[PDB]
RNA sequence: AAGUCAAAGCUCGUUAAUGAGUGAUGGCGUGCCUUUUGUAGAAUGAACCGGCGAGUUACGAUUGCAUGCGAGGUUAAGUCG
RNA sequence: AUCCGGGAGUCAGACUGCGAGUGAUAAGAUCCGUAGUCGAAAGGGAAACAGCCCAGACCACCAGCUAAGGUCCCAAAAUAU
RNA sequence: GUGUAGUGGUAGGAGAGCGUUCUAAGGGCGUUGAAGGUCGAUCGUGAGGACGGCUGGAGCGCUUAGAAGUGAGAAUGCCG
């Protein structure tokens, strides 16, 4: 034992940010977002305390898919029954249920335990153009990342 | 105050009136001790320094000579037939600090 | 000359047990399984005593990442400039400074910015 | 003249020629150094252990 | 030389070798004999020559 | 494979010393023995606790250590005890 | 390194560069020559992995430099020129 | 003192030690509580050793040497 800063539970203060997704490839937007959420960029990082922030994503319809993957990046599922493999979707979810897109392409790039789940419910993604959360005064981030 | 010191192979942050544990020193219980090397002088006017800020010392006295608790290291190899057994009590000399940089 | 086996064994076994207080079931009242558990615990203790020294470097590194990057200094170029301007702070102290004494950390970042600028 | 010789590798997995050339000079552990004169035989040993040892020409 | 202070001539009495008492002596589990083979049963070994 | 390293909180207060109990959460991690080129093996043995349970002795032979005499050493059977 | 003497285990090997045989210039095949490692070797890389690449743990520390391999996120480091 | 150097390892060879019962001499403890049992946050590099609290109620330590029915987790072991 010696002296190294170990964040407690409540001392950490979270903020609110608003990020656009207008003409950005899916990968990199998700990457920046996922890095912000886990609590990095805060020198008070602690690898078992949830020091994250709250992210709000706008215009989830105008997200960009480079080349093909408009009609080739085939998602999947399986219903745990014989012959249940339902590959239903494609890069069509941009149209419909556009929340589903980022809510997988990020719920992948996180850890896989409770911390990596309670660190996921801080996500709020809106295909539209304006959020209802003005009750909490979110700010804006930029992307040259 | 606020200062940084090289002892053993490590650094430490030092403040007036608080003790500090370090490695053995070859000095007796209750004599003065001076550390040569400083790397920073903090507080409210940071004196950053090229290695070993020139002309900065740290007094302080020694109060005890005592070892730690045992760190048993028994090794064994499975499917074969072997154990080695060990023991250890590392000695560390507690040091009370007074009169940071003069 | 018949040497009986009076109490040479219980000393040994009950010395093993006490070394296994609080194991998740019948691994604290079975003189056969307590021993195997103690053995594996010894292996793990040894290995991880060599990992306690690994992590804290990766941890201080991530913290220097977070704090430094805010000043436009990537976590490489900061260390590079520092080891170029002949400044030799130890990572642990750099992490501590980055967390607490923001003014001093920014002073160092300024000196480094000046350093590799040459 | 003289030569400074330093081990810069490991011998694990390299044959006796390399091992028994090294041992003959005084190279036991990594980054151990030995200073030797420059005959026309020492340079031969160095040419046979080039890849395992870097050398300054003092 | 008194009864309660006896000392033997130094280097004049060895100790013994009791074989098969635990893997630290170096002679447990096959009693310094190795693996199978009729040199390793009870009373193995062939006649002389 | 059920732990160890890291650790918030909660309750304590000892052979008095860098204290004890528990433990949210993170990192890492495929028992023990035997036989085998090779083991977590889906090769083979143990239900658990306790007790007993395996290189010894007599007579020869040989080499090292030591001790008493040394061109010498040395008794056996047997008698008194 | 040689010589004299006291005490043994070993005689079922495996894969991988290389050069040859039988095979069908097939086999994690079989049988030899030669080098390493495994057997008797833990730590890093190859997602996990005896035999591949790097390297041989007496012990302690919440210090520093590098090899193989790497530098968007899981996961430490360049969204480098 | 101080320098130099080395310290993975199965079959196996070598060396030094811990512990149990008994015998011999010397010196000791014990109803003002011995052996044995339980608990404790203690000591040595190891095997291991002390100290204190409770139970228990008649014999046991320590030093030097000697002799061994002297050390157990596995035998589809044997007895409860």
Image (tube, coloured by chain):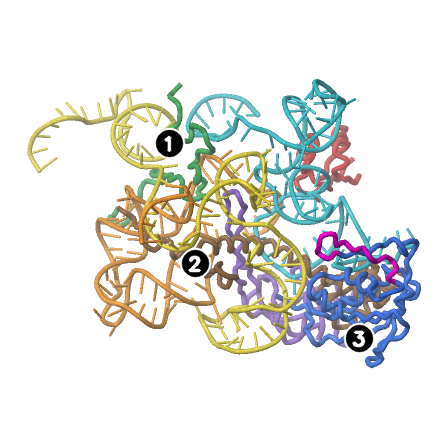
Chain colours: A blue, B purple, C brown, D red, E green, F yellow, G cyan, H orange
The residue under label 2 is: C15
Q: Position of residue G43 (x, y in %)?
A: 65, 49
Q: Does A19 sit left or right of C47 as displayed? A: right
Of C32 and H36, which appears nearest the observer?
A: C32
How many angstroms separate mark 1 from mark 2 (CA)?
37 Å
Q: Give the answer, above or below, for where F23 lies relative to F11.
A: above
Counting every numbered tag in the picture gives 3
Residue in the image at 91% along x and 72% along y: A129
* Chain assignment, label 2: C
**Secondary element at image label 1:** loop
Which label belongs to residue A90?
Answer: none
The residue under label 1 is: E42
Residue in the image at 70% along x and 56% along y: A80
**Secondary element at image label 2:** helix
Q: Position of residue B10 (x, y in %)?
A: 67, 61
In this rendering, the label closer to the viewer, 2 or 3:
3
* Chain assignment, label 1: E
Q: Position of residue C9 (x, y in %)?
A: 38, 54
Q: Find the magenta span and give its range.
A: A78-93
Residue in the image at 69% along x and 71% along y: A7
- Label 3 packing within 10 angstroms: few (<14), some (14-19), many (20+): few
- Observer able to see residue A144: no
Q: Does C59 sit left or right of F72 as displayed? A: right
Q: Indicate whether residue A81 is drawn in magenta.
A: yes
The residue under label 3 is: A15
- Label 2 packing within 10 angstroms: few (<14), some (14-19), many (20+): few
Of C110 and B102, which appears nearest the observer?
A: C110
- Callouts 1 and 2 close, C-beta under 8 Å: no
Q: Main secondary structure of the magenta part?
A: loop
Tags 1 and 2 both on a single chain: no
How many angstroms separate mark 3 from mark 1 (CA)?
81 Å
* Chain assignment, label 3: A
């Amino acid at each position: 034992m010696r002296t190294t800063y170990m964040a407690k539970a409540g001392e950490v203060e979270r903020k609110w940010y608003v990020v656009d997704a207008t003409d950005v490839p899916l990968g990199r937007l998700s990457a920046v977002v996922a890095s912000v959420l886990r609590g990095k960029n805060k020198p008070t990082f602690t690898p078992h305390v949830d020091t994250g922030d709250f992210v709000i994503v706008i215009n989830a319809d105008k997200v960009k898919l480079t080349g093909k993957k408009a009609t080739d990046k085939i998602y999947y599922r399986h219903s745990m029954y014989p012959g249940g493999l339902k590959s239903v979707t494609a890069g069509e979810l941009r149209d419909k249920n556009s929340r589903r897109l980022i809510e997988t392409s990020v719920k992948g790039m996180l850890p896989k335990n409770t911390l990596g789940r309670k660190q996921f419910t801080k996500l709020n993604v809106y295909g539209g153009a304006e959020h209802p959360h003005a009750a909490q005064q979110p700010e804006v981030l930029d992307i040259t990342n | 105050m606020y200062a940084i010191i090289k002892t053993g192979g490590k650094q430490v942050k030092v403040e007036v009136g608080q003790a500090i544990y370090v490695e053995k020193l070859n000095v007796e219980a209750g004599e003065k001790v001076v550390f040569d090397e400083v790397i920073l002088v903090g507080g409210e006017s940071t004196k950053v320094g090229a290695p070993t800020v020139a002309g900065a010392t740290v007094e302080g006295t020694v109060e005890k000579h005592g070892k730690q608790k045992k760190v048993v290291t028994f090794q064994y190899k499975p499917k074969k037939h072997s154990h080695r057994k060990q023991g250890h009590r590392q000695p560390y000399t507690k040091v009370m600090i007074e009169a940071i940089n003069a | 000359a018949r040497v009986k086996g009076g109490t040479v064994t219980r000393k040994r076994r009950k010395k093993v047990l006490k070394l296994a207080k609080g194991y998740y079931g019948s691994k604290h009242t079975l003189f056969k399984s307590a021993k195997e558990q103690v053995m594996n615990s010894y292996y793990y203790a040894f290995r991880d005593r060599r990992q306690k020294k690994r992590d804290f470097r990766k941890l201080w590194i991530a913290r220097i990442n977070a704090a430094a990057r805010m000043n436009g200094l990537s976590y490489s170029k900061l260390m590079h400039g520092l080891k170029l301007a002949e400044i030799d702070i130890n990572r642990k102290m750099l992490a501590d400074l980055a967390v607490n004494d923001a003014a001093a950390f920014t002073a160092l970042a300024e000196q480094a910015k000046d350093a590799l600028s040459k | 003249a003289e030569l400074k010789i330093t081990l810069k590798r490991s011998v694990i997995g390299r044959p006796q020629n390399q091992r028994a050339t090294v041992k003959a000079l005084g190279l036991g552990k990594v980054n151990s150094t030995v200073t030797k004169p420059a005959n026309e035989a020492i340079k031969g040993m160095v040419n046979t252990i080039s890849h395992l040892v870097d050398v300054e020409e003092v | 030389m008194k009864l309660h202070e006896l000392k033997p001539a130094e280097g004049s009495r060895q100790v013994r070798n009791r074989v098969g008492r635990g893997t630290s002596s170096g002679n447990g589990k096959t009693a310094g004999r190795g693996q199978k083979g009729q040199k390793a049963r009870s009373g193995g070994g062939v006649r002389l020559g």
